[PDB]
Every structure is written in C-alpha cells, then in structure tokens.
Image: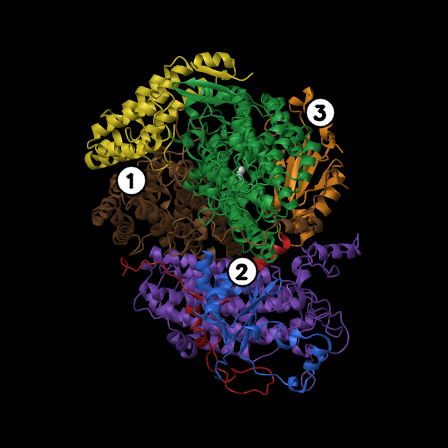
Chain colours: A green, B brown, C yellow, D orange, E purple, F red, G blue
C-alpha cells in the first residue's frame, strides 16, 4: 500500500532480463531470413553468455579504458612507438590494415548470422558479435593511427585504405577473411567465419603474432590485439550452437563436410603463405618456425580439439589438409619470392634476410639455402637494395622463365617453376577468356561456380603499363610525391623514387599470352 | 621451467633493444603523421571518428566513392556482388559522405552506454531503498504500464531486428556504424522496459513481470494491431536498406514510437505519480535523438541533397513516406484506443490533451523530416485521422 | 595490349557519351539489358571492356534510375519492371524457371540471365533481392549436391573449357 | 608433458621435424581431449594464474600446463579448465563479476561457456555428447 | 639540443637495464604480497578499499585504535593536538572500525560521479531536442518548482558546508572519506538544482534562473524558516564532528530533507506533468541512500554498539536526536505551508496525502535510525505535530 | 506554450552553474570560521578554475582511467 | 633563450666553482624573476601540444620559451607567460578536448595560473596586485 513496501536494495542483473529474451520474438509468416541458405533445420539454441546491451557496453568499455590508458599514457611516455624493429614496424602496416578488412567483413558476415538466426538469444549473440567486429575494425585502425603518430615511418601506416589497392597481395586478402565470408550462404557463416575463421585462424593471426611483436619491440600490438581476441571467445560460442543444429539434422549435415573443406581451403590458401611470410620475413627476431606455429594452432589444437572431436559426429578431417600441410612448410617461402620480387607494388619496406636469418631459415627448413637463399643473395648482388641499380627482380624472373600467375579463385600469386608449396598451373579458356587456376580445390570451385569468381587480377588491369606509372596513379608515394612508400630495404638512406623505378623499364605482361 | 622459449622483449631486453636501436634511423622517413590524411573532412578539422572509420569499407570505383578497383574476389552463387548498387534504390556520388554528428566510433559508443549501465543499477538499488514506488497510481502501474509498456518492448525489438539486413547490405562504413549502434539502442530499449517490469515485481507483491501478457497484447490487442503490422513490414517485408532505415527511424519511430514512448508512457507517468518510468524513458528518448541526428544526416544532408541524385532520392523518399506515414497514422489510430482505459486527466487524456499530443508529434515530424525532403503534409488532417480512433 | 589509366580512360568517357544520349525509360532499359547481356557474367558476348564494364554499368544504372523518377508514376517504381512487366509476375516466372531446371548447368544459366535482364533499376530493388535470394537458394542446393562427385577432368568437359595447359 | 606447447613433434627440428610433419599418419587430424586457454597478461590475470590455476586449478587437474608467451599465458589441459570469478574477486579485493574476468580471457580452443560466476572451457561437445 | 641531460630510462636503456638486472635478486625477499595484510577485514577477505584507506591516519595509541606512539610533533597554540579525543563526545575502542559499505575510495567515487556527469549533459541535449517541457504544468514550473525547489538548494549547500570542520577534525581515514564524499554529494545537489533551473531558462522565455528569488525565499519565507534555523545550527553552531554528521544526515536530512526532495518535489513532479525534475531528484536520492549506508555504519554498527561505549554513545545520540528531531518537525511544520500554494490533487496534496507522506518519512526514519539507537518515537504524534502547520 | 518550444539541443556547462556559486552563501550571525586565526581581513575572491562537482569527477576519473590502465594493463 | 635553460647560469658549474657561486653573498636572498615554469606530463595529447603548439605558435609569439625533455615530463620555462588553448589542441587531436581535458596532463606551474574560456595560461603577473 501507500506505507508498507520492501525497501531492501535491489537492482536487476543481466541474467535476469536475459532469460526473457527468448520470449521477445513473435510468430508471423514473413519472419524468416532474407538471405539464401542451404540450411533450414531447427536452430532454437541458447547463448552461453548472458549478455544484454548495457552489460555488453560496460564489459567492452572496461576493456577499452585499460587499453587506451596503456597506449595514450604509459607507452607514449616511454616512446615505445619508435622502439620497434623496422622490419616489424613495416609488418604491422600490412598485418593491422589487412586484418582490419577481415574485421570489417566480419561485421557484415555477423549481420548475416544475426539475420539468419531464428532464436532471439542467437540474434542477441550475433548483435554483440557485430558490435565486436566494429570494435576490432577501430582497434586495427588505432594501431596504424598510433604508429602513424609515433613510429619512424608513418608512410603506409597512414594511408593503407587507398595504397593497399596497388598491389597483388591485397587482392587475396579481400577473399581470405572477407568475400569468402559475406558472399555466400548466410548460416554457412557459422562454418567459414566461425568454426574455421574464428576457431582456427584468429589464434595465430591475432594472438600468436603478439609474441612476435613483443620479440621485435612492439608493445602497441599486444595491447590491442590481445584485447581483440578476448571478444572471439563469445563469437565461436555462437557459431558452435548452430554447428550442433546442423550436425543433428541429417538433411543439413550432408552439406557440412563440403562447406568445411571449402572454407578450410579458402582461408588457409591465403593465410598460410601470407602470414608465415610476414612472421618470418617481416621480423628480425623469430619466435619459432611458422610451420610449428601452424602445426600447434592449426593442425594439432584446432584440428584435434574442434574437428577431431567433432569426428565422433560425422565431421571429417578436411580432405585438403594434406595439401595444406605442404603449404605450411614451404608456401610462405614461395610467397616471399613474389613479395620481394614485386616489392614496388606494396606499401611497406622489406628487408632481405641477413646472414643470421639465412642460417635460421636453413636450420629450420633444410633446403632453403640452396633454393630461396641463393636467389635472394643473387638479387642482393644485382643491387636489389640500391636505387641506382636499375634492378627489380620481377623482370629478372621473366627473363629466366619464372612467370608469376594469379589464381583466378584465391588471388594468391603462383610461380610454378620455383614453388615448393602445393600447386600446379591449370590454364583454361572459357568463352574467350583465359583463366589460371593453381590447385585441385580452387579449380573445382571455379569449374562449378564461374560466376562467383570474376576477379580482375593485377596483370589484366596493368597490362602494358610501366611500373612507376601504376604506383604514382595509386598514390604509392610519400608526402614529397616522388619517394616510394614501398622500399627494398629498411634503412633511412637511399630511398627509391618513381624515377628510380622508371629506369628499370618494368612493363606488365599478359602471363597467359603464351597459352 | 617450460617447454617453449621465454621470448625476450625487444623493448626491455638489453641485447635486443641495442640491436633495434641500431636499426632504427635517426630521422623520420616521412612527415605526414595524420592517419588517412586524405579523408575529406566534414567539419573544420579531421576527426578521430573519421580517421578510424572512413574508407574501412573496401569499395571499388564502381560503387560510388570507392577508391579500389576491379571485381570482388568471390560473389554469391548467381553473381550478387559482395556489396553492390542493387542493394538500394537510392543513388549518390559518394556513399562515404555520411557522418554521424555524434562522431561515434565503437569506443565512445560503449563508453556512454557503460555510464548508463552502471548508473542505472545504482539508481535501482537506491530507488528500491527509497520506497518511492509507494505513491504510484496502482491502476496505471498494473493495468496500463505493466501491460502496454511491456507490449511496447516488441515494437522496439522488431525495429532492432529490422537492422540485421542493413548491417549486411549497406554500402559504407559510417552508415554501417550508424545502423548497428541504432539497432543495439533499440534492443536496449526492449531490454530496459523488461528491466523496469522485473524491477517493479521485486517491490510489488502480485506484480507479474512475465512477458506473457505484454506479448499477447502486442500480437492480438487491437491497440497494437497497426503498429505490429508496420514493424513486421519494415523488418521482414523489404530489403532496401535505405528504405528500412528511413521507414524505421524517420517515419514509424518518429511518429508512432515518439507518441507511445514520450506522449503516452513518459508524459502520463508524470500525471499518474510514476516516479520510476521517467528514469527508463529518459534513456530511450536520449537514444532516439542520438539516432535521429545520424539518420537525419544520412537522408537529409547526404541523400536528399546529393548534387546529382537529390531530387531522384526525394522521389523515392517521398513515396516511402507516403506509404509508411499512412501505416503509422493507422498505428496511432489504433493506439489511441488505449486512452479509453486510462483514468481521465484534463489536458492529458481528454480529447484536447490527445489532440495536442498528436499536434506535437506530427508538427515536430513535419519540421524534423517532412520539410527537409519536400514531403507535404497537412498536420491537422493527420491529427484528425488519428482522433477518429479516440473514444470520447 | 596496353591498358589506359584505371579510373579515367577513353573507354569510360566514350560510354558516358553514349549514356548521356539516352532520353527515355524504354530506351535506357533496352540499353542496359543489351549491355548486361553483352559484357557481364561468364556468358557475356565480349570481354573487350572487361576492366571498365563494371563502372560503365553503374553509370547506365544511374541514367535509367533518374529517367525512372523523372518520367514514371510512383506506383510503377514499386510494382513494375521498366520492361513494363508486373514485378511480382517476373519473380514468379523466374523462380518457377529455376525450380524446373534439371541440372546445375541449367539452373546457373537461369540465375545468371535473370540478373542480366532484371538487375535494378530494371526490376524494383525489393522484388529483385527477394527473387535473387530465392534463385540462389536453388542454385546453391543443386551445386552442393555431390560437390566432389565429378573428377576434375569430367568437370572440365562439362564446363566446356578449352584446356590450354595442365602442369605435369 | 603431452600438454606442453613444444610437446611431441614440436621438439624436433630440421629434417626430423619434416619427416614426422609429412608422415602419412599425420595427414589427418587426431582427436584431442585437450582444451587450450589463453589469458591476456594483466595485474588481475597474473594473480589468477599464480593463486588459482597453478594451485587449486592444477591440484584438481594435474595435467594443466601454463607457458609464458610474453604478452599472454598459454594454458593447455586435459578435459577442462575452470576459473571462478567469485574466487578471483576474493583474491583481488575489488568487484569482479564473470564479465570482468572475461576482460582478459582471449583464445579458447574448446567449448567455452559461463555458469553463474564460473567460466569453463571444456572438451565436451554439449548438445552432441551426454 | 637542450641544456640538461636527456636521462636514459632504466626500463629501456640497454646499459642501465643490464645493470639493474644484475642488481635484482633472482628470488623474492618475502612472500607476503598483500598490501597492509594486517588490517582486520570487515568482510570475508580484505578489500582494496580497506588496503588503500585503512591506517592512512597516523594516530598514536592514545587515540583509540592508533598503531603509532608518542605526542604530535607540533600542536596548536595552547596545546590542542593535531587530532585528539576532545574533538567529540563519542567514545569507541577503535576509530578505524568504520567501513563504507559502498567501499568508496577516491577512484570508484569519481568514476561513478563522472558517469552521472556525462550522462546528464546527453540527457539535457536530448530533452531540449525532445521538447518534453511543453507539457509541464506552468504554475508548478514557475510558482512552485522554480521558486521553492531553487530555494531548497540552500539547505543542500548549508549541509555541504557543515562538513568543513568534520573533514579537519574527524579521527580516522574511512570516516574522513565518507564525510568528504557526503559533502561533495550535498554541494552537487545544490549545483544540480541550479543546473535544472538554468536549463529550464533556456527552454521557457521569461523564466528567470537567477537565485535572487530562491535566496529571498530561503532567508525570509516562513516556509523555510525552521529548516534554515536548523542547518545554520548544524553547520555553524556546533563542532563535535559526530554531532554534525548525525544531526546533518541521520536526523535533519533523513526527515526534512527526504520529505522536501522526495515527498514534495520528486513526488509532486509526477502529478503536475514535470518530466524534467525526476531526472535530477533521481541523483539526490541516489546520493542520499549511498550516504546513509556509510552514516548508518558509523553510528549504528561502530558507535551505538561499540563493545565498551555503546550505551554511552546512545546517551548522546539520544540527546542529539531529541533536539534535532524537534528542530526538524518544526522545519516540516513550516514547510507544509507550501501545500497551500499548490494545485490540489487528491491523495497527494490534500490532508490525507500529506499525512501519508509524513507517515512514510517518520515511519521510515523510525526503522532506519531511531530503532537502531533505542530512541523512542511516536510516529503518529510527529505526523500530527507537522499537520498542525497544514492549512485545510 | 504547449505546442511551440525551442528544440535546439542545449545543456548546461560547468561555468554556467559556477557563476551562481557566490550567491549560494547567505548571511547570518554565526557564519564564520570555527578555527583560531590571526587573519581577519576581507577575502571575497574568485577561484580561477570554474569547477563544479560533476566536472570535478569527470576530469579526475579521466586521469585515473589512463593511470590505472597503464598500471594494471601495460 | 639561454637564460630559461634548466642548466642555466650557476647550473653549468660543477665542483668548487658551483659551491663558490652557490655560497656567494649576493645569492643568499631570492632574486625576482619574470619567468614562469610549466610542467607537462608526457602523453599522446601533450606531445602533440608540445611539437605543434608551444614549439610552433607558442615560440613564435614568445621566443624566450625553452622546452626540455625530463623523461616523464616536459619542462617549459619562458619570460612573462605561457599560453595553451584547449580548442587549438582539440582541433589538432580531432577529439573532444576542453580546458579541463587539457588539464589532465598539466602538472607543476611556477607562476600565476588560470583559465579563461578554452585557454590555459600561466603568467608572471601578480593578478590582484599588479
Ligand atoms: Fe573480430
Ligand atoms: Fe569474430
């Protein structure tokens, strides 16, 4: 009544509103996903974390305050921004901005999981994931923004959202954790984004990399990236719930193994060579061989704890695994050939392996010295680092019959005459267009689904054009308008200019003209 | 000990720090330290909001404003692009132009909402200790607030889910952020209404915070019939993501939503002695104005006045407004039937009171949205059309 | 061959001049359909403007869409394709088309051609996206039936490629 | 010892590693009963490592291995890893809900969930097992 | 260059870091890592609040609970000690026992208030944009709220300044913190009232936010005559710091303050259509309950039940309560004359409504304070003493 | 009136409140210090930073979050 | 200007030379100085302020300004006054930045310090006496 009431102090915990979320949906005929999917089984699942909006915000904001305290206050007062080894500070231009687009695409894929979820609790989870993926886009951007302010080379930290478009390594990044998520079956994102992408590849990509950063003097990236991954544990919990629903109903389970192998191959095709190259060639101090990192995170832990355990329930070890293990051992060395050979098209300054590096490469990958090692040492002899040399190794590859091809499906470069990783060139003509495919898994994808895979490659866009003109047109220059962002060494002197590139007379060919 | 190497930190280990210092040049290699310096600033100086958000979306030159080139690497079966112009009827010279006037990237967004989250719980712990619920009109509390405010959570929840395809489909970074923050704010509204109900249940024996009655009212009570039909259409009947955002926030929620939240539940709380509900509506109405600021920029500043497609966009926005304003007028006509259930308060619940509340909502909307896209509207005609649903 | 600059070149300029001369909805509609049949998708007639066709398509869409708002009654923008057909009838026709397809090769061409003919602004966006998702559902399901069932050599025969090179 | 980061093949280098890496038996995944948990280093986490996982945690699960990976702790264990935010809040002397424990919990290879104030990462496949 | 050395950091400079590493022992020199491990914990385990606050005050063994020894190094002219037992009539076995149940050291205190600070400005920016002031009863807004709510800021301000001698004189660290946090919360209340008035001034032309009329009413209007007499006495008439805190928070503010803030301005706002004032009273009432938690611990758990001085302390607390409760019922008797100026609302402003409001205030206070110190009070008698000032 | 109002977004900055603080005191006989002093001169001065309680909390909390982030995290 | 150097004047001398001036008869009473000294706590925002405000426009208007690197903070000494506009700083930082946010990292101030709108200044003037 007007006088008597319980005056005990009470609030309402997030758990207490959360148990009512399932009742927030209501039935009407049009209440179903807008996106095409193969998966129509029952998916009325409970989310494993009792997150509501206010608590979502409290949780994430508490993370940010600590992170930005460490960046803007502590590490700035220590001058840590310039305590990074140049190889690694250059590597974070690529890793943070490339990951940034993976995060940005993950917002869109998580919105597809939100849209295709049928249970209100799973819509709740995917909303938080969508927000997290926005958080991670701004975190990756903050890393380069911070480096832009405090690191000795802001060029390329400070404009990658336009300068990435110059080079060929960025094409395949728009697939690996990007188009490959959002351009396809929406509930299949529980498999490609989550069960493969988040459960498998974020761990080396986002966590393991912080040990390499630290080894090389970067305490910025551990501060941000580790925080990023704290959100990932909620993400995969969402996806697992759906994977269970798929596994349990026989009509959906008959798609899961093919979607899993396709997603595994699609992500590892780019991730394996590119991240291994950035780790091992974009560092001075190495933590461990890339192939062991891959063995530990990808093959043994993700492979056994997720896939092998799901084997009890009909999920198969990816048929492409054997081809992938060959990639883990050699493909990043293959890619280094292309990366160093085509250095003017990037936005980072590279460093040929020094004598210490080369011994490490040969100790850990015997045969490196007699193959990759001798090539890099000849390039150095020819003036690879010297802007007056007139030497760019891409022209040298062609003059020795080492053509570079772009995979029509994955966009990953391939040098068949020098590769030790998985691959063989297939060149098909279809309706007057020539196409180069590079492995059994992607070739099947293109043969079955040609209208999904019409990505123009750098040779088709740049055909007949001289290198310095492509670079200038794409704004691949420092603020003086002439000195390249990209460099074949990491020293402060003898930086290459557009005129230095021009003297080499490199003009883009049609690699399939010979077929 | 441990199996793996204890990696030495380059920042602090003497040998690695000395090696690093010898490798780092004594001079900067460029002077341009402004992250993405080439962004065209909306305001007098480039903001951190813009630096962190603008051009994260990797659009090619064939989606207006894109700096990239070439086709996507992988498309849908059939050929649907990862993002494409087919996603909406509206056109522009640059999909990146949009700027939230609150300049919310993720961090300021959760920072502000964290404040509300923690302070809400401190207020509830003290409100329960205060015993201030003792003076609330019990009929309002039990028959109107619990039942019909509870039912309103489903309108907020539907508008929240309307954003799922917008978050996938929309064509730039700042738009995607504006959309998703709006969606969280909508589902927050729904969770906050349910929080208030759960909170009252702890103070009032016999008060049932279950959503069974609110859900029955949302799904079958004629008072919400028009509102639910409109929300279902905006959420699940369309996929043009601009139409969803415009119909959702700029027509339906700015007319029906503002009437229900502000003219009915918030306003009438302060004539029925409800010292609790104003604390919750303060949040939903703050979120409404923050969302309105960003929705207004996208459709008024950017699309309705785009130098090449402004009039073209106003043609569509005029057509959507015509359709969804009719829908919202129908939702309000149904909704004012609720006044036949409330205790009469002169100037609030009689015909003059409801007439003035509809004049504020429709008058405000004419100023805030209709006048800015060239949509003509007779305010009195719309007020009178709703008052036909009012039982004297 | 030698490509011109990426974002500003004679091909794009020449097509903008062609586009500027469209003056009715029917004319721009035949223009965009003919363009899309000739130059887009793997079954296009020509790759001669390959690195420019996507931008050029956007500019035709822009011309057709403004011609729509200038010239058509509002009801037409919502319910009709610029061919004059009823939009709902177009949806029903092509969903039935793809559901009657006997093989993934039949179904894929039905989907691809639907997009060539009715991609917005020809068909209203809401009807197009719903129709396009319905078709993609069918094409995905049939394609993902026994995905690894046909060896590569048979897949290549079925696709009808001319195999120019297979590395040993 | 089997839960060490450099367990098994990870001990080998050069040719010996390559031989086992490319051995036929190792071209398919092998089911593992392990979980892997990564803890972001911080004042609160380091206390949790020293006084919870390496005491009560390892006492209940002797198979847990904690390795120092510079910016984070890498923890592998048979079956499951559990951390009670209520117990952690008692060590830290400050408010500490399960959501606050998650501030610095990153990678989770295994099925992660919360139950009240406890966080668990488990080998069990809930909804499939049991 | 620069004139002085650019000092090399031992954390990062290779040479100095190697020297430091060689000097640091390979093992800890003790295992006790709990800061001030010897504090007796109030709760199951020592809190950071206790570790940071407890025994900061360097009391000697002759101020009960002190761990130091000897006389102060410098005393006042005459011999008054830096701190001393002469500062209060109350005695205890240990001045350090007090624990704020909110466990506020400085950081959580400003953290919470910062949240409220930033969210208030967002709410006002949205409330002004919302236009919700349009439905407030103008008589209430202009003749009652502006004038007498404004005038109440001087009660809050007077109670704030009552704490000045408390912050100097009180005898332990945790007491000093609750005292000072309570003082800031009171001047915040006063500033928030003035903030609300300044805000309405921006929305309502002719509305005067000057404190001239509020000050004239506080200083001369018979409605606040009893109240002003009491805060002047509590603020400037006494220096026993326990008497100030007890009379200030536990008697005067718990009766007059709670009635004016919660029963009059907050409650009546929600019968006169005031959608603005509840947002501000929500803060003052939250602060009241937080302050009450710490005041209750000091006087009930620590002093009224001190194992050796409990009854001795109750003798004084009973004498103070008798005096300042008389002062407060007189303040309330004056204050209920304000009801003669308000628009009549049955159950709120009639005799029955004010009687039930006084039954809540005096009834709640009997439970919250009187019953815990053994102070006898007839609630009905006090209600009737105040109702003698109510004009029918 | 009840239909027309200025709906421009406005708040109240700290200095807007601060300018009225001087007016918060009021005159009464016992309104003087409790402590012994030699210094009895007039001292009606203005403070140089326009700080109110809400703003005080906001600035200090801001400092704290950065400090404790550096300590507890980095 | 060398006279505002931290190691100016007597501070250059060592050993007996320093002792001789330090204990000189004339240096046993204070000497009026027209200088101010301001300490800025190092941070992202302050470091931007130092390089682009006090060392650019600041020293343009006041050439006597000396800025010294003291590891964890900047030491600033100038004749007459030092001035920092929070609005100019916020334009430089592209994020909300009032005079109270500027003061987050403004520490020691030897002189008469005050704020006037968005501007912080420390002056040698004796406000209320001069
Ligand atoms: Fe992410
Ligand atoms: Fe994720």
Percent position of residue B286, x then y: 40, 53
Percent position of residue C160, x then y: 42, 13
Mark 1 or 2, closer to the camera: 2
Taking depth in this image into account, of A383 and A89 the one nearest to the observer is: A383
Q: Quadrant of the N terminus of chain D?
A: top right
Circle 2: is it few (<14), some (14-19), or many (20+) Cα within 10 Å?
some
Q: Please, what secondary structure does the residue beneath circle 3 have?
A: helix
Percent position of residue G18, x then y: 69, 77
Q: Is residue E160 visible?
A: yes
Circle 3: is it few (<14), some (14-19), or many (20+) Cα within 10 Å?
some
Taking depth in this image into account, of A320 and A372 the one nearest to the observer is: A372
Q: Which residue is mark 2?
A: G47
Q: Is residue D61 left or right of residue E339?
A: right
Circles 3 and 1: CB distance less than 8 Å?
A: no
Circles 1 and 2: CB distance less than 8 Å?
A: no
Taking depth in this image into account, of C68 and A307 the one nearest to the observer is: C68
Q: Is residue B206 visible?
A: no
Q: Which residue is mark 1?
A: B324
Q: Is residue C72 left or right of residue E56?
A: left
Name the chain under label 3.
Answer: D
Taking depth in this image into account, of C151 and A33 the one nearest to the observer is: C151
Distance between the alpha carbons at the discs numbered 3 and 1: 67 Å
Q: Quadrant of the C terminus of chain D?
A: top right
Q: Is residue G1 above or below residue A456?
A: below
Q: Which mark is residue E243?
A: none
Q: Which mark is residue D20?
A: 3
Distance between the alpha carbons at the discs numbered 1 and 2: 53 Å
Pointer 2 residue Cβ closer than 8 Å to ligand 1? no
Q: Is residue E156 above or below residue C17?
A: below
């Amino acid at each position: 009544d007007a006088l008597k009431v319980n005056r005990a102090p009470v609030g309402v915990e997030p758990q207490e509103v959360h148990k009512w979320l399932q009742s927030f949906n209501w039935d009407f005929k049009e209440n179903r996903t807008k996106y095409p999917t193969k998966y129509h089984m029952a998916n009325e699942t409970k989310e494993q974390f009792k997150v509501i909006a206010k608590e979502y915000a409290r949780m994430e904001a508490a993370k940010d305050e600590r992170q930005f305290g460490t960046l803007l206050d502590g590490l700035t007062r220590l001058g840590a921004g310039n305590k990074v080894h140049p190889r690694w500070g250059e590597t974070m231009k690529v890793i943070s901005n490339f990951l940034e687009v993976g995060e940005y695409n993950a917002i869109a894929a998580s919105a597809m999981l939100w849209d295709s979820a049928t249970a209100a609790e799973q819509k709740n989870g995917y909303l938080a994931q969508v927000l997290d993926e926005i958080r991670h886009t701004h975190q990756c951007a903050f890393i380069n923004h911070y480096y832009s302010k405090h690191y000795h080379d802001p060029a390329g930290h400070n404009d990658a959202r336009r300068t990435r478009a110059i080079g060929p390594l960025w094409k395949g990044m728009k697939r690996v954790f990007a188009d490959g998520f959002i351009s396809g079956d929406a509930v299949e994102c529980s498999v490609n984004l989550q069960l493969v992408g988040e459960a498998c590849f974020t761990n080396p990509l986002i966590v393991a990399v912080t040990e390499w950063a630290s080894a090389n003097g970067d305490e910025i990236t551990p501060t941000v990236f580790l925080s990023v991954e704290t959100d990932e544990l909620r993400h995969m919990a969402n996806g697992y719930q759906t994977v269970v629903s798929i596994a349990n109903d026989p009509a959906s389970a008959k798609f899961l193994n093919t979607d899993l192998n396709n997603a595994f191959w699609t992500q590892q095709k780019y991730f394996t060579p590119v991240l291994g190259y950035l780790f091992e060639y974009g560092s001075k101090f190495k933590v461990e061989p890339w192939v062991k990192t891959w063995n530990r995170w990808v093959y043994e832990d993700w492979g056994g704890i997720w896939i092998g355990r799901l084997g009890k329930y009909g999920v198969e070890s990816p048929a492409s695994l054997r081809d992938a293990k060959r990639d883990a051992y050699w493909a990043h060395h293959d890619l280094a050939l292309a990366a160093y050979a085509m250095w003017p098209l990037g936005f980072a300054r590279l460093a040929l392996p020094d004598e210490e590096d080369q011994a490490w490469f040969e100790a850990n990958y015997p045969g490196w010295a007699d193959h990759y090692g001798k090539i890099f040492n000849e390039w150095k002899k020819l003036g690879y680092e010297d802007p007056k040399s007139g030497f760019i190794p891409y022209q040298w590859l062609l003059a020795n019959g080492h053509d570079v091809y772009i995979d029509r499906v994955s966009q990953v470069p391939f040098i068949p005459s020098l590769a030790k990783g998985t691959g063989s060139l297939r060149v098909h003509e279809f309706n007057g267009k020539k196409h180069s495919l590079t492995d059994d898994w992607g070739e099947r994808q293109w043969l079955i689904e040609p209208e999904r895979y019409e990505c123009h490659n750098v040779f088709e866009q740049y055909e007949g054009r001289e290198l310095s003109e492509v670079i200038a047109e794409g704004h691949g220059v420092r603020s003086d308008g002439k000195t390249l962002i990209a460099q074949p060494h990491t020293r402060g002197d003898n930086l290459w200019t557009l005129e230095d590139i021009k003297r080499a007379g490199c003009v883009f060919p049609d690699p399939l003209a010979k077929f | 000990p441990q199996s793996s190497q204890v990696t030495k930190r380059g920042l602090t280990d003497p040998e690695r720090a000395a090696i690093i210092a010898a490798a780092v040049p004594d001079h900067a290699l460029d002077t341009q330290r402004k992250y993405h310096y080439f962004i065209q600033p909306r305001w007098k100086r480039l903001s951190e909001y813009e630096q962190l958000s603008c051009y994260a979306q990797p659009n090619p030159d064939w989606i207006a404003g894109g700096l990239d080139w070439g086709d996507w690497t992988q498309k849908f079966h059939g050929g649907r692009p990862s993002w494409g112009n087919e996603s909406t009827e509206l056109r522009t010279t640059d999909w990146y132009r949009h700027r939230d006037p609150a300049r919310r990237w993720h961090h300021p967004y959760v920072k502000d909402k964290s404040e509300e989250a923690r302070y809400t719980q401190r207020f509830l712990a003290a409100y329960s200790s205060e015993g201030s619920i003792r003076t609330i009109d019990p009929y309002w509390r039990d028959e109107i607030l619990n039942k019909y405010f509870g039912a309103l959570l489903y309108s907020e929840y539907g508008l929240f889910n309307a954003h799922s395809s917008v978050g996938r489909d929309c064509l730039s970074d700042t738009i995607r952020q504006t959309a998703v923050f709006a969606a969280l704010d909508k589902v927050d509204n729904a969770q906050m209404i349910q929080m208030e109900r759960l909170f009252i249940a702890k103070l009032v024996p016999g008060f049932d915070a279950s959503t069974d009655v609110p859900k029955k009212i949302w799904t079958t009570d004629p008072i919400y019939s028009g509102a639910r039909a409109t929300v279902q259409e905006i959420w699940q009947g369309v996929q043009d993501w601009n139409e969803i955002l415009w119909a959702g926030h700029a027509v339906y929620d700015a007319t029906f939503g503002q009437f229900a939240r502000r003219e009915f539940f918030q306003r009438l709380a302060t004539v029925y002695g409800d010292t609790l509900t104003p604390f919750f509506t303060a949040q939903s109405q703050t979120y409404f104005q923050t969302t309105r600021g960003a929705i207004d920029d996208l459709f008024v500043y950017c699309l309705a006045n785009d130098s090449e497609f402004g009039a073209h966009n106003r043609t569509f926005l005029n057509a959507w407004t015509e359709h969804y304003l009719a829908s919202s007028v129908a939702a309000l006509k149904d909704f004012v039937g609720l006044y036949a259930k409330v205790e009469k308060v002169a100037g609030a619940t009689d015909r003059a009171g409801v007439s003035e509340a509809l004049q504020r909502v429709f008058g405000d909307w004419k100023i805030d949205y209709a006048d800015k896209i060239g949509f003509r509207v007779d305010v009195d005609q719309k007020v009178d059309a709703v008052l036909a649903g009012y039982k004297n | 061959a030698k490509r011109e600059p990426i974002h500003d070149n004679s091909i794009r300029t020449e097509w903008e001049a062609k586009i500027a001369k469209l003056t009715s909805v029917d004319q721009a509609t035949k223009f965009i359909q003919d363009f899309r049949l000739a130059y887009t998708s793997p079954f296009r007639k020509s790759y001669d403007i390959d690195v420019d066709y996507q931008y050029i398509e956007r500019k035709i869409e822009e011309k057709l869409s403004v011609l729509k708002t200038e010239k058509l009654p509002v009801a037409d923008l919502i319910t009709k394709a610029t061919t004059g057909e009823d939009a709902a009838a177009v949806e029903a026709t092509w969903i039935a088309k793809i559901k009657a397809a006997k093989s993934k090769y039949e179904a894929e061409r039905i989907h691809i051609e639907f997009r060539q003919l009715y991609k917005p602004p020809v068909l209203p966006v809401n009807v197009f996206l719903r129709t396009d998702a319905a078709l993609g559902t069918v094409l995905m399901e049939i394609r993902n039936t026994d995905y690894y069932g046909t060896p590569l050599e048979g897949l290549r025969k079925e696709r009808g490629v001319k195999v120019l090179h297979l590395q040993a | 010892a089997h839960n060490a980061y450099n367990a098994g093949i990870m001990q080998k280098t050069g040719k010996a590693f390559a031989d086992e890496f490319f051995a036929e038996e190792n071209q398919v995944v092998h089911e593992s009963n392990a979980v892997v948990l990564v803890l972001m280093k911080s004042d609160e986490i380091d206390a949790i490592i020293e006084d919870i996982v390496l005491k009560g945690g390892k006492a209940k699960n002797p198979s847990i291995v904690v390795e120092d990976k510079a910016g984070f702790w890498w923890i592998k264990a048979d079956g499951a890893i559990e951390i009670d935010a209520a117990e952690a809040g008692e060590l830290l002397g400050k408010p500490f809900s399960v959501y606050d424990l998650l501030i610095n919990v990153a990678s989770a290879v295994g099925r992660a969930y919360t139950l009240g104030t406890k966080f668990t990462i488990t080998s069990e496949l809930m909804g499939l097992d049991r």
